Image (cartoon, rainbow, N blue to C red):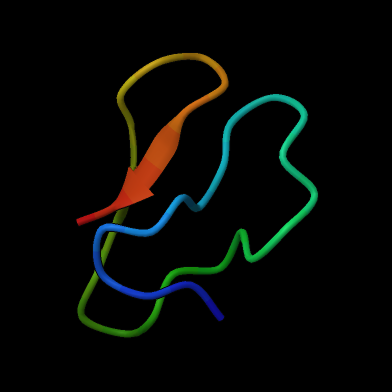
Length: 36
């Protein structure tokens, strides 16, 4: 699971894409999305 300020990931991120409950995956850039 991804944590707060962590990268939930955009196009091409195969890591922790699922943000923790209480954080949202926000697309900041097409490849960089962060769990806020």
